[PDB]
Image (spheres, coloured by chain):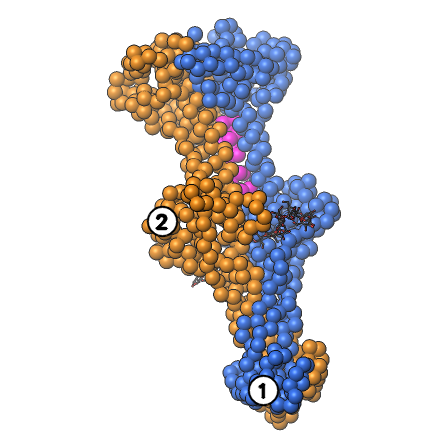
Chain colours: A blue, B orange
Amino acid sequence: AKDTAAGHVTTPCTEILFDLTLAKHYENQIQAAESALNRNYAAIRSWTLLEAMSSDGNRQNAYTGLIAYGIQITVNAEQELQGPKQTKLRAAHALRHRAANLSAALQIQAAQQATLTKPTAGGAQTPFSGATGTCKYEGITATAGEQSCKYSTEDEEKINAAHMNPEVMTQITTIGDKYLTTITLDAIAGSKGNPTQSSATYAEQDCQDGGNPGPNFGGANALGLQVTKLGTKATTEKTNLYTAGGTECEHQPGNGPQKTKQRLAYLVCEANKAAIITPTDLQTLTLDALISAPEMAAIGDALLTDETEKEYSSAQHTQIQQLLKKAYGQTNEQFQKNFIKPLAAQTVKFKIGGAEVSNTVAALMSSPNSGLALAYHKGK
Amino acid sequence: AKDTAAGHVTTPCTEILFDLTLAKHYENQIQAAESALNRNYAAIRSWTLLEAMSSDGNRQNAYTGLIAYGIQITVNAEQELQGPKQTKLRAAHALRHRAANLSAALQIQAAQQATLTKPTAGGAQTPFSGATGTCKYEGITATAGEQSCKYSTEDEEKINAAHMNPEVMTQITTIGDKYLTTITLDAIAGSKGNPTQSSATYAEQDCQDGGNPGPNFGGANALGLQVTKLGTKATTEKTNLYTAGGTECEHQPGNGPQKTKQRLAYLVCEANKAAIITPTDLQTLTLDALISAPEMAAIGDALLTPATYSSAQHTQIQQLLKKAYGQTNEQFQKNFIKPLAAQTVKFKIGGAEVSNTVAALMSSPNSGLALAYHKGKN
Ligand SMILES: *[C@@H]1O[C@H](CO)[C@@H](O[C@@H]2O[C@H](CO)[C@@H](O[C@@H]3O[C@H](CO[C@H]4O[C@H](CO)[C@@H](O)[C@H](O[C@H]5O[C@H](CO)[C@@H](O)[C@H](O)[C@@H]5O[C@H]5O[C@H](CO)[C@@H](O)[C@H](O)[C@@H]5O)[C@@H]4O)[C@@H](O)[C@H](O[C@H]4O[C@H](CO)[C@@H](O)[C@H](O)[C@@H]4O[C@H]4O[C@H](CO)[C@@H](O)[C@H](O)[C@@H]4O[C@H]4O[C@H](CO)[C@@H](O)[C@H](O)[C@@H]4O)[C@@H]3O)[C@H](O)[C@H]2NC(C)=O)[C@H](O)[C@H]1NC(C)=O
Ligand SMILES: *[C@@H]1O[C@H](CO)[C@@H](O[C@@H]2O[C@H](CO)[C@@H](O[C@@H]3O[C@H](CO[C@H]4O[C@H](CO[C@H]5O[C@H](CO)[C@@H](O)[C@H](O)[C@@H]5O[C@H]5O[C@H](CO)[C@@H](O)[C@H](O)[C@@H]5O)[C@@H](O)[C@H](O[C@H]5O[C@H](CO)[C@@H](O)[C@H](O)[C@@H]5O)[C@@H]4O)[C@@H](O)[C@H](O[C@H]4O[C@H](CO)[C@@H](O)[C@H](O)[C@@H]4O[C@H]4O[C@H](CO)[C@@H](O)[C@H](O)[C@@H]4O)[C@@H]3O)[C@H](O)[C@H]2NC(C)=O)[C@H](O)[C@H]1NC(C)=O
């Protein structure tokens, strides 16, 4: 059940797909948390206008309670996100950098056929100081066409963010370092007769001397070489994320130099361990969620009591809760109606310095006229 | 005079430096704007608390004007940032991707010396069907030590964000494509006597037999080869960022396939055009900045006394603003700016003692709680 995604990595292209998919996963987690913060801050702006439009002291106090609750939880969550966000971005960055690296090495290791140039025949020249004949080539090249990664339906099912929850990941798979450092080639030389400096008929891209030079080794004395294949084998390597106990990161830095895969496993381990805590969605808050939130015990005592310093007893909390039900309604439907539905449904319109505003509450408070509408209504 | 940084790109490592430096420039432009938005919202939370602790209705009105002005300008700048942010991030990503690509190619193109394997002596075999001897090698390899980019202080001064304003950038410099696609090598075959399939003494990583084999074709018959040099030479290419008018981006996508360098040029040009406007810093606002901000005309008219503005009305609103916020900047600083860091706020409610300055408290895990306490006393 574990390691479905990493266990499917067998090739440069599938490691690339793993590396990019995991990077986007972490990036998506940061985005979802920040969109949730954005919605919470937009709700607090909406309730700030609604408080400014209340004439009821009790309703006014109810909106102020939601502003105070939302500010506390959203500011706290934004502050809490910063550590995990930076840990997850560090991993995502390295994974995309590794995938780029591999994609470039993939293009070069795909160059598997050589283009021979016209050699020059010689005698005893370095590095063959004991040869009687040498055939010397310069600027042999090997190039492949533009390489692309192509993926099977199985590839995309297994190497998928659905398989990248922290609880199923114990290892990563990487292509071995020689794929990124080493050129590998096969070559063969061939001799015939007595190749010498005179073996200077090159039409066959070799060094043919003096018989009837021509195709294959036509001349009585021929010498040549050919690079017959190039390309380094991509071998796969496994790296563990955790130590024996299953909790600590295995490749913590500071224990000497590390292979690329060891650096990556550490970053992935820490990014998996850095679970983001997404705050409550204010815009879809429910009455029972609100009254059960422990922050609303002290906030309710601040706004809804008449007269507590010390910590609340059981009877004191249940008092605060009934005050909370009075302020916010006794049923969710009332709560939704008077505090949630006004965000999208309540219409606000005004006109001040020659500037007509006609929006609904949440859209207006996230618009260029937002602060002008707050000043207008706090002014009446 | 223009293109100082791109004009210093002469090697793979200086293109890498240029690519990363420009990417960080775009990234730091976004971070500067988003850092301003963060400080603004934290100022607005600070003034929200200062308003709730205010007993004077007129001083309360003043804080609500700062709250309203800040929310208006910060919400607007946040929304305006999103387009340019995405355009600059598109460029920064691609530039970091190119730099990674070029770094990986450099590691491979630095492999300049081969290690031979032990060969196998043959007779005629493909691709040498006429040979009397062949000497066949499998898995010859070329590897460099770990490559780094070493930069001079002149590199870092010329390839620098200070040389990457939009007005000085007309081209980019890139290493030509063959550096990233093509292996280049030199090789030489050597023969002596009559090499045959019996030339199976391989101590020299060549094929020898007869006589006294050993170094430099010591045997009576010998054949072998050596790859004496590897590495493709990196050449530079220039790409223009703008079309003939000098304002619209060249190499726009949707005109057939493009070279890597042309895709990069378009992204850089659009990122250069997508200028980010950083909002006014609320936490360091001066009085003249506040009263002369055009948003404060309507915002003062709404809270300080509202027409639905002549020359006169604008004069009237200005002195209304000086009335609320101060006649001097030292007063405005003292009453509205300095208390964010200098005014300690304390209280006690939920069995929790809380003491902090205003701005720190309104960004702390007790921020909303402090707001409910003071709006509750009021
Ligand atoms: C760092 O270093 C790395 C490593 O070297 C670099 O990474 C490489 O970068 C290159 C260049 O970007 C990559 O190669 C390009 O890949 C493009 C993306 O393709 C994917 O996504 C697109 C969606 O945008 C999708 O269409 C593709 O799927 C197609 O192919 C699969 C596989 O068969 C198939 O399942 C799909 O059905 C699609 O097939 C259609 O299209 C194929 C051609 O693409 C046809 O062969 C097929 O019959 C079918 O029609 C894929 O999922 C891709 O768009 C690029 O292809 C372009 O450009 C090529 C030249 O570069 C050219 O040879 C191709 O023919 C194609 O050109 C055509 O399409 C483009 C885009 O629409 C048009 O602008 C052109 O005008 C042209 O259109 C004609 O042909 C059309 C289709 O035939 C036709 O409709 C139209 O009418 C026209 O006649 C490249 O393949 C490469 O993948 C990367 N490699 C690796 C290993 O990562 C990296 O760049 C570098 N980074 C930096 C910053 O330096
Ligand atoms: C994608 O592919 C990429 C391409 O393949 C790949 O990139 C490569 O990554 C590797 C791995 O990270 C890189 O190698 C590492 O490079 C580190 C940095 O090396 C350079 O800088 C060092 C520090 O010296 C500078 O800074 C000092 C302090 O500020 C100054 O006092 C110096 O004057 C000097 O300043 C100059 O350079 C600064 C940076 O450019 C610059 O800010 C400043 O202005 C000024 O210009 C240098 O020491 C180092 O030089 C070493 O190597 C060069 C080779 O050219 C020699 O000429 C020198 O003689 C010297 O030996 C570079 O200039 C290294 O720190 C790091 O080294 C450690 O690890 C390796 C093994 O991996 C060991 O061999 C080495 O000894 C080090 O190990 C030890 O020390 C550490 C302490 O840090 C210790 O913890 C550890 O236990 C151990 O004891 C390593 O070599 C490589 O550079 C990248 N290459 C390229 C082309 O980019 C990338 O990883 C891939 N990415 C993914 C995701 O896969």
Q: Residue at x 37, y 58 (%)?
A: B152
Residue A75 point in image, percent of width and height: 49, 27
Which amino acid type corresponds to the residue marked 2 in the rendered image? Lys
Q: Is residue A152 left or right of residue A270?
A: right
Image quadrant containing the N terminus of chain A:
top right
Residue A191 point in image, percent of width and height: 64, 85
Outermost residue toward the front? B244
In this picture, is A322 found above or below A278?
above
State yes or no: discs 1 and 2 in contact (Cβ < 8 Å): no
Residue A86 point in image, percent of width and height: 51, 40
Between A254 and B168, the one lying in front of the other is B168
Q: Chain of mark 1?
A: A
In this picture, is A300 found above or below A238?
above
The label on residue B2 is 2
Residue B367 point in image, percent of width and height: 46, 23
Decide whether the magenta segment is chiefly helix, strand or loop: helix
The label on residue A199 is 1
Between A189 and B312, the one lying in front of the other is B312
Between A131 and B259, the one lying in front of the other is B259
Whether discs 1 and 2 lie on one chain: the answer is no
Mark 2 residue element: loop
Magenta stretch: give its range: A73-89
Q: Residue at x 41, y 52 (%)?
A: B6
Image quadrant containing the C terminus of chain A:
top left
Which amino acid type corresponds to the residue marked 1 in the rendered image? Ser
